Image (tube, rainbow over all chains, first blue to last red):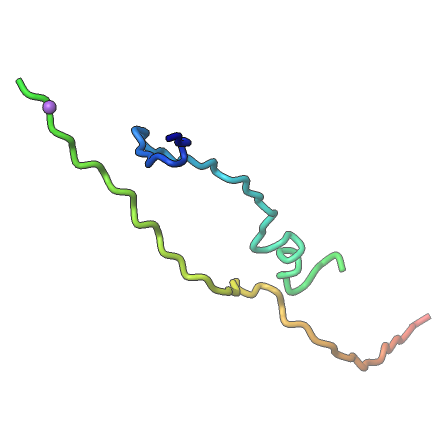
Length: 48
Length: 49
Ligand code: NA
């Protein structure tokens, strides 16, 4: 008779190692207080 | 001599469990409270000439 390799049970001598790449990441600008908020926190503005 | 028998292999960590959720982050308020006012006064000028 005749067989394909898919017709034979396959065992592996290979040791698995699943390494995945660290993904791209985007850092958006972030501020707790903008400089306009810091300017506006004063009660009276001398210039205005 | 004999060969060392197979060692106990390490175990992959369980992995950090994460709770999904929605959040609102609040900061200390530094903006003054603002409102609208109306001033009624009278400019009084006395000129000695
Ligand atoms: Na041995």
